[PDB]
Image: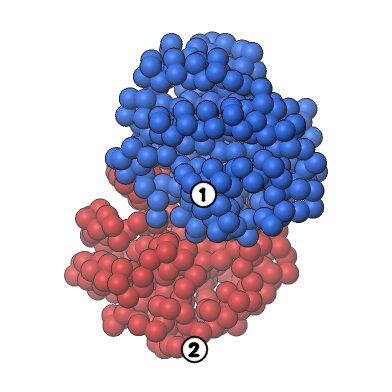
Chain colours: A blue, B red
Amino acid sequence: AVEKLTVSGNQILAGGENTSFAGPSLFWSNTGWGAEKFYTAETVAKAKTEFNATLIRAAIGHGTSTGGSLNFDWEGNMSRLDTVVNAAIAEDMYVIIDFHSHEAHTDQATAVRFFEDVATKYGQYDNVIYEIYNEPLQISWVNDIKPYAETVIDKIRAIDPDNLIVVGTPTWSQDVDVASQNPIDRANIAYTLHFYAGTHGQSYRNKAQTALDNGIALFATEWGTVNADGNGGVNINETDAWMAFFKTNNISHANWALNDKNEGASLFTPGGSWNSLTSSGSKVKEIIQGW
Amino acid sequence: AVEKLTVSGNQILAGGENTSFAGPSLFWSNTGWGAEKFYTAETVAKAKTEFNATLIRAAIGHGTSTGGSLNFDWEGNMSRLDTVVNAAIAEDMYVIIDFHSHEAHTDQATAVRFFEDVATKYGQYDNVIYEIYNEPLQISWVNDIKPYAETVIDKIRAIDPDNLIVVGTPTWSQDVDVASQNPIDRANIAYTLHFYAGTHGQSYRNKAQTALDNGIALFATEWGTVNADGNGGVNINETDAWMAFFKTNNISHANWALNDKNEGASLFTPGGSWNSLTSSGSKVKEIIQGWGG
């Protein structure tokens, strides 16, 4: 079993203690996107045996115009999610169930269908963390994200009242400072912080510091060692600064991405696996093992 | 009236004869989960006229942290159970009173309260079958489920001495083989077997075969035609393999679920009912209609 997660002030506690976790985020689960082969019990087990990962993020694709997402292949994506959630439970790992969207607030009925379904099927496990809106775009925290979040949080809680729910923030989950000015009044809510080391430096870390100062807890559900588009070289200086910032604030995180697509963010070289890591995979392996 | 159910060896006898029954299982009764609307006398009557069902399972939700369950809305869930139980008696159908839990052993006071209440109100009827623990998870049969079971069976039996009691087994009620190695010394006890045709195949029937060969009777109180999680396409051939295994061994069963949630396991389309069946609903109707009821 894993320890139950709760929020106290700007800290996420596990079993009442200050600590944090690290693991990999799987790439989009979308049919046709090439990462379907990683949504397996074998892959979840390997994240643990190879990297000593304590969590895994299932990025379930959503989008009315996004090919192979939940709007096109509900069954395929939901079956991949089920396999990963059950494996995480079997491996004593946390599983972040991510509604991987950039438009959740405009396709609310689908978001509610997804969350009521996951709360019903997996809510009883303390391993389950709900990430309700991956990356809102340049929208309003108070008028667009917050109302959607309150609605979804309440729908999940009528089924599964106990859990940690992580809510996306404006501008690809960078505006945690804006969200911190008007937090959501519900128990155990944390806010999403996303960054790519090759593009987001100190000023982005300053925004996160403002959020912590304002009293909200952060969860870096997605971050990369390369540039923001998921490619380019590994920026060790910035990666190390962000990791130190997370370590000294008990901020948990998931690296993008356990995949083999031909781009720098992939943990594996194309067609490769755990024995053939990319420059990013090599750095991530050390970070997760030393967490 | 219906015939009295008893157990002899690995068989469940009805009026002393080998036979089996089929029907639908309602979805969680929980307040706010969208299936409360199905817990009606009309639904019980229609299960009999539309599908020839000879039983109906009432999945009364339980859970200390399961929203809308008996722990949060006792009266609402109990009232829904009452409506279904009385209608089953009025329609000469068996009713499986299911304490729909994944944590009954850890909330015994609630289980005892529930069972003493149901045994007092309905124990006089032979239509009543008690299912004391829907689906235990990764727990021990000898150390966790069995002691809980003995306690609950004794509380029920001090009020209603005659009845069939079905006991959950480990790993979502799959480990009937494990339970068969250390059976309960109480009369008329059967053990729960659950499976989903799109996920569980011959290896799971082999575990059930081990249990039957070891001397215990099984009752498949919950099963699906699609994948284990409740969604997906109907696996016709696997469903047929399981129905043949049940027919030949006279194993009674209840299909999950009489509901309209948009998932493969629902018998009905969203906002639908008897006249608007899903692919699973059509297959289940075919099985129940020709079972013998």
Q: Say which residue appears at 49% left-offset and 89% top-offset.
A: B213
Q: Say which residue appears at 50% left-offset and 58% top-offset.
A: A91
Using a 10 Å C-alpha cutoff, classify the residue at mark 2 as few (fewer than 14 neighbours), some (14 to 19) or many (20 or more).
Answer: some
Q: Say which residue appears at 63% left-offset and 55% top-offset.
A: A43
> Which of B19/A190 is in front?
A190
Q: Is residue B111 left or right of residue B60?
A: left
The quadrant in which the C terminus of chain B is found is bottom right
Q: Residue furthest front?
A: A237
Which one is in front in this view, the residue at disc 1 or the one at disc 2? 1
> Which of B120/B191 is in front?
B191
Q: Is residue B267 left or right of residue A260?
A: left
Helix, strand or loop at disc 1?
Answer: helix
Helix, strand or loop at disc 2?
Answer: helix
A33 relative to A140, above or below: below
Give coordinates of residue B97: x percent, y percent. 38, 59
The quadrant in which the N terminus of chain B is found is bottom left
Give coordinates of residue B219: x percent, y percent. 47, 72
Q: Is residue A52 left or right of residue A46?
A: left
Amino acid type of the residue tagged 2 in the rendering = Asp
Q: Looking at the rendering, which quadrant does residue A68 occupy?
A: top right
Numbered label attached to residue A84: none
The residue that mark 1 highlights is: A289
Q: Say which residue appears at 59% left-offset and 47% top-offset.
A: A285
**Residue at mark 1 to residue at mark 2: CA–CA distance:** 48 Å
A146 relative to B172, above or below: above
Q: Looking at the rendering, which quadrant does residue B105 occupy?
A: bottom left
Q: Residue furthest left?
A: B158
Q: Is residue B74 left or right of residue A155?
A: left
Instruction: Return the chain for callout 2.
Output: B
The residue that mark 2 highlights is: B213
Instruction: Return the chain for callout 1.
Output: A
